[PDB]
Structure formats: structure tokens, C-alpha cells
Image (cartoon, grey):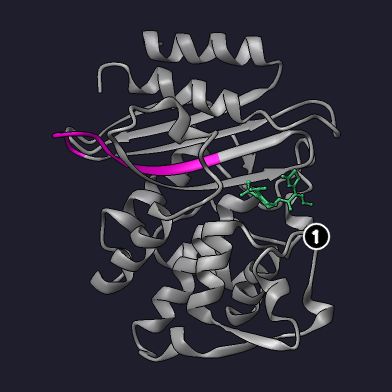
Amino acid sequence: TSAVQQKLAALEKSSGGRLGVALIDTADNTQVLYRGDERFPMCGTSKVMAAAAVLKQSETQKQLLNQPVEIKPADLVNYNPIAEKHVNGTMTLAELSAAALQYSDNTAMNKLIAQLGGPGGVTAFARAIGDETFRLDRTEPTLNTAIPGDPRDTTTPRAMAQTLRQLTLGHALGETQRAQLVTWLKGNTTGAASIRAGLPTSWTVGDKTGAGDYGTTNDIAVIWPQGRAPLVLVTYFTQPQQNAESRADVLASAARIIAEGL
Ligand SMILES: CO/N=C(\C(=O)N[C@@H]1C(=O)N2C(C(=O)O)=C(COC(C)=O)CS[C@H]12)c1csc(N)n1
């Protein structure tokens, strides 16, 4: 183990939970992993895969993002900050993607999942871009149950870091679609206390958070440091008590550790 991994282990010990980290440094294509091949509940970080899958569809259906989708009262779930403003109205697939990614709207995520034919359609897209680990099994809100040991709606930090790299810096998506995803991630509103809080303020960051039961608190980010090659960082955290409070500070701390030297 390296000093980085040792610091992450110490953070984990003090936190009382289980911490998973994967950093990809595109400068030399190296990876730093902590519990990198253990499965963790994704919660809302899975919204990146769903939005990306719809972007992929739009590469051959060029008007798809503009397609209005009906929002019915019965569609609302447990957290619908944007969709609730469109009950008995519509949101386009672009608007649903922005809401799911930038506000972590759960109704918006369910519409993306439906557009893909269900959770299996999101998983199928993951497989198509070379992610053999990701699995989406449920819709919102049950995909965030985060039960210890439950393989449903999980991935590993290594796999999610590799996929996030391919989606944003690589070419799993077409050029316009890649840029659109990056724009959405950069404009996220929910990440100020997570990875962003542990990085220098001059660094540009795009991220997607997630949260669930068992105090599950997650963040995945693409990072552009000042005058250096970009990084991808996944920080997953989950706890023993079903009713544990969120711990965004732990993600900020992991980011602070990872940033040393970069
Ligand atoms: C059964 O589902 N339980 C959830 C849940 O809906 N998580 C989802 C997820 O991931 N989300 C994020 C997210 O991206 O972190 C926030 C972010 O919240 C805010 C106010 O920005 C809004 S809720 C949504 C849950 C358990 S604890 C918590 N906050 N949510």
C-alpha cells in the first residue's frame, strides 16, 4: 500500500463506515484505488449512466433530446424538485437529463429509465461501452436502499471511474454528446459539500452525488486542475446503521487526501 491508501484507511477507520475510492490520473494513466474492486450502492451516481444512455440514443435520433415527455401526478416519487413544477405538463429528455443530473431529481431519473426500456436498458448501455460491472436493477426510489451485501444497483469504484473517464474525457459518446454531459456535470447544484469541498477552488469540477439508506453518501467527479492533465475521482461511502446520517465531509476528506501532490 502507498501513503495515499494508508491515509484513506485512516479516514475510513475514523468514519466508522466503509469507504471506496478510485482516482484515475490521465497524465500517466495511473490509478489509485481503495476498496477499488468492492461493490458499493451507487444511489444517484447511477443517474450519469442513464443520462449518458439517452445521449447515446440521440446520436442516431438527432431530435430526441427535444422530445417532450408527460409528467403525471402518479409519476412523482420521494424527491422531485424540478418535476413537481411540471405535473400535468411535460419535460423534454434534455430537461429530464439536466434535472436528474443537476438537481438529482428522482422523477426525472425514472423518466430516463423508462425511455431506455427499464433498468436493464441502462445496464445494457453500460455493457455496450465496456463497463462489465455496473448494474441497475430498480427504479427510484428503491434503487437507493443500499442494503449491506445486496448486489442490486451497485458497481465498484474502479469500474465507475473508468466509465466516467470514457464518458467525459474519452469517446464512449459522440463529440456533441460528450460535451453536453460535461456541461451538465459542471453545472451540478448538489455537490458543494462533497468532492468539491476538498479540492482547490481554482480547479474546475463536474460531479454527480448520490445518497441513500445506511448513511450512504457518494460522489463521482471529473476534475481539471490548474495547468495539469485531468483526473477522474469516485468516492463511495456507506455505514452500518440503516438510519445513519449522511457524511459528505468524509467525501471531502477523501478528496483532500487524493489532491495532495496533484
Ligand atoms: C430511497 O431513497 N433515498 C434517498 C434518495 O432519494 N437519494 C437520491 C440520491 O441518490 N439523491 C441525492 C444526491 O444526489 O445526493 C439528493 C441530494 O439531496 C440534496 C438536497 O441535494 C436528493 S435525493 C436523491 C436518500 C436517502 S438520504 C438522501 N439525501 N436521499
Q: Is residue 76 visible?
A: yes
- Residues 244 and 156: in front is 244
Residue to which mark 1 is pinned: 78
Which quadrant would residue 148 be assigned to in this image? top right
Residue found at the very far front of the displayed protein: 85
Determine the residue located farthest toward the left in the rendered image.
227
Q: Tell me if 150 is positioned left or right of 58 in this view.
A: right
Q: Nearer the viewer, residue 129 or 166?
A: 166
Say whether residue 119 is visible.
Answer: no
Q: Find out if the beta carbon at label 1 lies less than 8 Å from the nearest ligand 1 atom.
A: yes
* Quadrant of the frame with the C terminus: top left
Residue name at image x 66 percent, y 28 percent: 247
Amino acid at pointer 1: Asn
Q: How many marks?
A: 1
From the viewer's side, name the closer residue of 17 and 195: 195
Residue 84 x, y percent position in the rendering: 73, 72
Image height of 194 relative to 47, above or below: above
Quarter holding the N terminus is top left
Left or right of 17 on screen, residue 58: left
Is 248 situated above or below 137?
A: above
Residue 168, image x, y percentages:
32, 56
Q: For the residue labelled by badge 1, is the local secondary structure a helix, a strand or a loop? A: loop
What's drawn in magenta, residue-wise?
219-229
Give the class, few, some or many, for how many residues have Cα within 10 Å of label 1's Cα (few <14, many ≥20): few
